[PDB]
Image: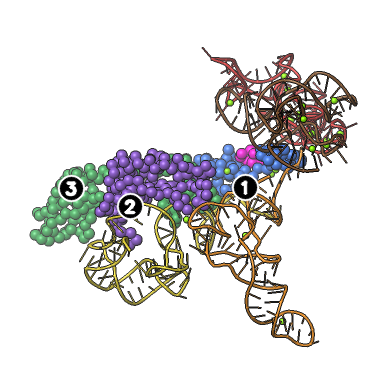
Chain colours: A blue, B green, C purple, D orange, E red, F yellow, G brown
Amino acid sequence: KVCEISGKRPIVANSIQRRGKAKREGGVGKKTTGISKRRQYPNLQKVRVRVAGQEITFRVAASHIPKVYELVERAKGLKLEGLSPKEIKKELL
Amino acid sequence: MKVILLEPLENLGDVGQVVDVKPGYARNYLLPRGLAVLATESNLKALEARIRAQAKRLAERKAEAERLKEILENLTLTIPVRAGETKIYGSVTAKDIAEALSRQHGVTIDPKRLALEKPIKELGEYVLTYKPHPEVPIQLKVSVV
Amino acid sequence: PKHGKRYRALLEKVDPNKVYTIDEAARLVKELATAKFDETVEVHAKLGIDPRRSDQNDKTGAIHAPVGKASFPPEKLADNIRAFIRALEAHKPEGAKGTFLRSVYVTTTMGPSVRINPHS
RNA sequence: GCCCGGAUAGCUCAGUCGGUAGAGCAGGGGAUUGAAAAUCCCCGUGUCCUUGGUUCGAUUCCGAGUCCGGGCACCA
RNA sequence: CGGGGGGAACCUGGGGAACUGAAACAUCUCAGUACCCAGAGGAGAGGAAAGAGAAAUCGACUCCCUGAGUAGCGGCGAGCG
RNA sequence: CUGGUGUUGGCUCUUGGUCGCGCCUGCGUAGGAUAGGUGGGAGCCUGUGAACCCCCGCCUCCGGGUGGGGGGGAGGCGCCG
RNA sequence: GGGGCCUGACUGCGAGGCCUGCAAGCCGAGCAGGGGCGAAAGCCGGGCCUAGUGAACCGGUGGUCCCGUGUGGAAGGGCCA
Ligand SMILES: [Mg+2]
Ligand SMILES: [Mg+2]
Ligand SMILES: [Mg+2]
Ligand SMILES: [Mg+2]
Ligand SMILES: [Mg+2]
Ligand SMILES: [Mg+2]
Ligand SMILES: [Mg+2]
Ligand SMILES: [Mg+2]
Ligand SMILES: [Mg+2]
Ligand SMILES: [Mg+2]
Ligand SMILES: [Mg+2]
Ligand SMILES: [Mg+2]
Ligand SMILES: [Mg+2]
Ligand SMILES: [Mg+2]
Ligand SMILES: [Mg+2]
Ligand SMILES: [Mg+2]
Ligand SMILES: [Mg+2]
Ligand SMILES: [Mg+2]
Ligand SMILES: [Mg+2]
Ligand SMILES: [Mg+2]
Ligand SMILES: [Mg+2]
């Protein structure tokens, strides 16, 4: 899916199949036996973390996980209660 | 992946101390149970202060003492006690001491911070330290009449 | 023990891990030669060449030979040292691949050895 | 095309951890059973492919050339 | 306070063919076209240089004319540009 | 199906690779003898406590090499040959 | 068929023709350089002749008056083999 912070989301890429000694050395050159469409997903995971009276879960990219914490921190200085674990999330930027 | 501790943990401890753990240890064990905080430069300065407020401000309750010894130290007390030669008909507690010391001169002392054990009573002659840490031995004379 | 003290004392003015120049050590070599005779300061350096290489020093790749006494002035050691460096850099085999002169020590007849950069 | 490994008795296979080259089996004799051997004994023959140079020369170590053995690729 | 639904084309974004061409065919071509989806508006996009490229140079972006079928790209083929 | 990585963290036991360094290693005729090459090479080595004896780990071409230790006492040792 | 010297199984060209849809194939006197055999006349740009062969493209090597993306140099090309 998409990252709840980095915004990163799946993208389109080609799977190019090549054969033959490069020209970069050996000879004649490389050759494309065939190209194909395929996706490239974000290495997103999940990060659960207290933050007041709830736990709230974060489905976020790998290289962003840290920011999630630098957010439960910046959070601190603010009041957030009531049955609003979804809102807690909502609130944290 | 720096972190600032708390309870002095083996292999790395003494709260405030900074250490290089593995992201996993921090995120999943340390912070969860609260054994440390992320080495964010927001608490990395916040500790800079936590460290000065005590360090500098400490020069008073262990630095101003000098003002508290110069006045005294080279001083001499001597207090009127109802006695009978080498044996007083009562005693003088540290509390009994400053009691009048804060009227004979105008010096403030904390009794609970003095240094004698049993309550004077006897005589001969006295002289003993105040407190605390780098102290100042005072001089008091047991009077007559 | 393992060595005699006459040597144990010289180990006090020779950092175990430090490169010295031909002026910083050339004079420190004339002070580590504490024998009852006038010794001979020599230089030993390992050459990056192939031993059994017929067309390219003993049979392991080591260089020796002495060049100076234990009294010679600061301008006779610091100057005669370079006279041995270029004596080598003038015979580096064609295919002599590798740092031709990797390691270089300067020891006397009885004193220890001081690692030095024959380029300064 | 590159990286690897190598014949020495008839065949197969080890090597001062540089000078002292030695096994199985085949073959000769003798031992040999009812029968042929499985058992039993004792030895023949040479740069250890081999170019070398280090060393005291080299079979062994380096230039290394020829052939063979297995490898990984390329072929516009 | 707003939103939601619609609108002939035009518009930006997210996805995205095959026939066909190569006188077969897979790289290539058709083509980022057809089409699907979201969104915007009377337009939309873009927009004040972490630019261009050889000049003591220029000076946001967009549109037209050239440059130019040039430079190049290319089973150096078809063709693309 | 699979190796490397990210999500992925504690504590130990066990081994490989590499450079640092510290140590010994090496035993064919000859020869005091278990000689790795090459150079320096008449001075070293001991109250900065040696010659001799017992203990004691490791190595073994069973010959020694050699280290810890106690002991001991003014002497070991190389050249020349 | 035999022998003595030799390497013209040359480099730079090439008038003029044969053959022929193209492009290929073929013969070639003669001039220059530097050579070989001959006393010289001269002959020699492989083999008595007609088969023993493969356009381009892509690359591999060895050379080289060339190009080398602001400049120097490189990277990578061209040209010759
Ligand atoms: Mg997903
Ligand atoms: Mg792929
Ligand atoms: Mg990362
Ligand atoms: Mg060696
Ligand atoms: Mg062999
Ligand atoms: Mg049997
Ligand atoms: Mg409203
Ligand atoms: Mg509206
Ligand atoms: Mg198609
Ligand atoms: Mg077609
Ligand atoms: Mg689009
Ligand atoms: Mg245009
Ligand atoms: Mg063009
Ligand atoms: Mg296109
Ligand atoms: Mg023609
Ligand atoms: Mg003739
Ligand atoms: Mg001719
Ligand atoms: Mg012919
Ligand atoms: Mg002929
Ligand atoms: Mg083609
Ligand atoms: Mg340039």
Residue G14's quadrant in the figure?
Answer: top right
Q: Which residue is mark 1?
A: A46
Q: Residue at x 46, y 42 (%)?
A: C91
> Do pointers 1 and 2 mark residues of a single chain?
no
Q: Is residue A68 visible?
A: no
- What amino acid type is highlighted by mark number 3? Glu
Q: Which residue is mark 3?
A: B73
Residue G26's quadrant in the figure?
Answer: top right
Give the letter of the chain under mark 2: C
Q: Which mark is residue C69?
A: none
Q: Is mark 1 within 8 Å of ligand 1?
A: no
Is residue B121 found left or right of E21 in the rendered image? Answer: left
Q: Which residue is mark 2?
A: C109
> Do pointers 3 and 1 mark residues of a single chain?
no
Q: Nearer the viewer, residue B58 or F14?
A: F14
Secondary structure of residue under mark 3: loop
Q: What is the number of callouts on the image?
A: 3
Please state the extent of the stretch shown in magenta in the rendering: A1-11
